Image 1 (spheres, helix red, strand yellow):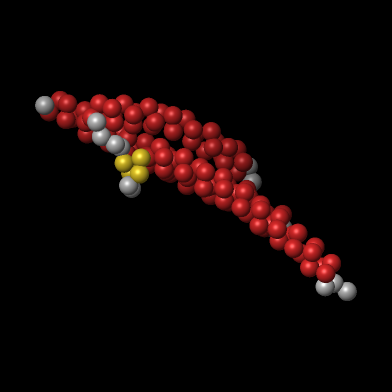
Image 2 (cartoon, rainbow, N blue to C red):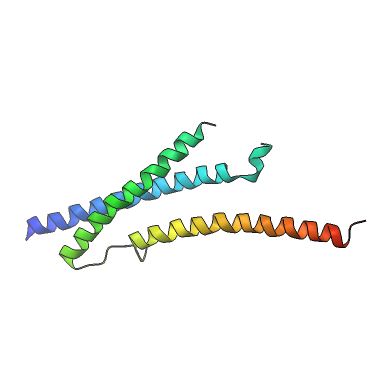
Length: 125
């Protein structure tokens, strides 16, 4: 009845609050990531302590949220979806895209530097 329905909605509101906290923390983390990774910074800051803080928070927020989501899904036989996706899959996707983006930026610089030496040798005077 109404007791069980209160619990449904209260726990679900809690899941959404965890989602919003995770997203906040993630987007702040990515801002510091961009600054820390900026090529311009050599010719452009205890923001490392802060960057590191957000970094340590994230997996803790994820483990807590993961446990609550699963509890709620099992009890109510429903998938917990956010913006059309199981939220923890969205979380994993975000991390891997970030990881891959970081690699791809390194790789582009690598290939660019390599072609620069190639072209300087083939056509240089």
